[PDB]
Amino acid sequence: YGGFLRRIRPKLK
Image (tube, rainbow, N blue to C red; front, side, top):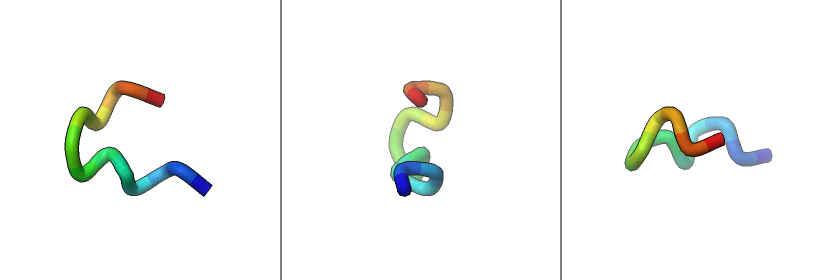
């Protein structure tokens, strides 16, 4: 459950 922490750095995972 780490798919919209992309809100900063949207290619980090």
